[PDB]
Image 1 (cartoon, rainbow over the protein chains, first blue to last red):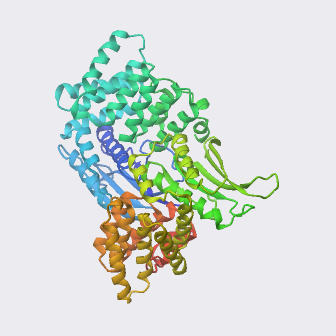
Image 2: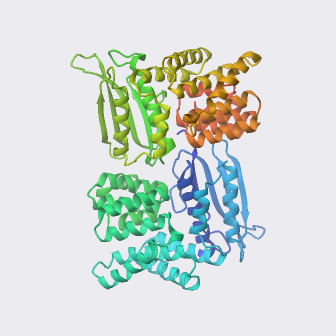
Image 3: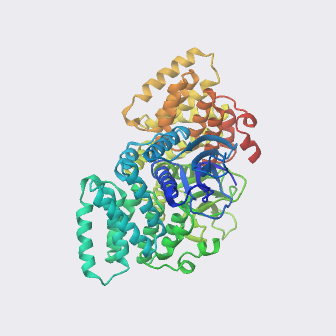
Amino acid sequence: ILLNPRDIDINMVNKSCNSWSSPYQLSYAIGVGDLVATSLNTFSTFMVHDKINYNIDEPSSSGKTLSIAFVNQRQYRAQQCFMSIKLVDNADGSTMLDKRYVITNGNQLAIQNDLLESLSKALNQPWPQRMQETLQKILPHRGALLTNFYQAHDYLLHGDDKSLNRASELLGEIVQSSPEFTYARAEKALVDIVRHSQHPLDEKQLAALNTEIDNIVTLPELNNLSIIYQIKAVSALVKGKTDESYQAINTGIDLEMSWLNYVLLGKVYEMKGMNREAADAYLTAFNLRPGANTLYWIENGIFQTSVPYVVPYLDKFL
Amino acid sequence: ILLNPRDIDINMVNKSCNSWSSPYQLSYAIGVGDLVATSLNTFSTFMVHDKINYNIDEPSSSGKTLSIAFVNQRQYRAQQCFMSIKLVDNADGSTMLDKRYVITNGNQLAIQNDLLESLSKALNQPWPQRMQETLQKILPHRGALLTNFYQAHDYLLHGDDKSLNRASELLGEIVQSSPEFTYARAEKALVDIVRHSQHPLDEKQLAALNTEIDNIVTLPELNNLSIIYQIKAVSALVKGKTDESYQAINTGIDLEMSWLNYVLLGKVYEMKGMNREAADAYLTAFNLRPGANTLYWIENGIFQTSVPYVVPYLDKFL
């Protein structure tokens, strides 16, 4: 296989460090990892394979690996686990970046902004204005909200009804505490239409939801964000408005190249009766973020999809 | 290997069709092929591996293959070769696009515009305004100039002094015949500074060249094109202005993701004394357009580069 220098794998190692993580700071590393992958995929000509949730260590054409590893002071063999982040050029096996981070009470944002600035330099990849404004709009600016928001994100990833109820409740507690974090209201609205899709005959819930949505998609602080087209795409899908769903989701994709946007495009293709196009979107989502969470969303997200029938290549690959 | 649906290989088969090609229409197919690869790489989130000039058929993670094959009416076993172009989804092995083109006296543009429109649909990839304006500026609009221009492009690809002299003479005959094809004057200026780099002590030629260049980079019809930053990048490199060279070439890359821009970035990194960064740019050029032409440009283009020392991974891969 020829290595491609513009092809980056993101890995996580030692998920069971020593002390003391734990979902405590694991959903943090997961969130930073996903944020990095999706920023690069959206705003640069790097292709990122986010393999944080992937079990198999297969052969890849990836010229760079970004590794997140949990490491204890060792001097004890197992204590307060520092976060080790290395960018390796797999062409030579040399280290282009080596960071060691200790989590604290108010450095979560710092750690992440320092990671982003440092990746910009190491990859000679300045970040476009559109990425800067996007990060400002999409992320809370206090550490504690960041912790809670990425925990919510971790429930969204799992994707089962129970997980979504918890994402939705966590996002509601965020919103009640900090009404000004508008993006979280947008995320809540999205988890909420996804949950409501499972109770199709509950029209009173549909009416409450159309209201929460209409009072979100109009907001100015959310103009030009993907979240807003994801909400419209799923809301239109649930209502059978396949063409509005298609146009919303392709606009969402233009704004955010995410595993989730491609799953949703796959769903819209299925509804349209175009299974080869669906399979294509799904295998794209799976390349972007391979593993059980994406697999679960392909198979169950919004409605059930038979992977043997719609995406046989993926059954055979796994 | 997991197939990536956003990863496209461009192949050429039967380079020795039957009747009657021949460089006659081979440099045409080559030019269309390169144009497709570089448009997709620049203006979409597809990664294209342009393997038109590549001998080895290795294992790739490519989810789609675009094949250019020369085929004779067969009914004779070998006659006027039609151009067969198929887009295959390698996930299922199904055909997403199947075109058969016969070359004529005034359909060369037609064939190419029809290919582009048809790729847009088959890949659900509308083309951005920036691509449309770019194609308008970068391509002549009569068939015969297109023939000549792609022949010139084919000499540029080979990259040796003799080839460049011929590119330069062909582009000059184009310019003399059609002064309004401004892009060709820009291409001539570029081949010309590259050729002049081999005669460093010829100051009279340097003065003529600074004049042809200054009278090109200013032109308005060329604003926002890569060619203009390629000219500045090479002109600055030859003059030892490494920082101007770096800034020009990174702007060129933003505007055109081409094998050649990455070779030139690699050259600028070498001059700067940064060989791991050079190796990276070079292996990127080689992923974009693998084979002897790109290899020749890495090894010889502007100045000589020792691949064993600067890019050992590439020696070992080959």
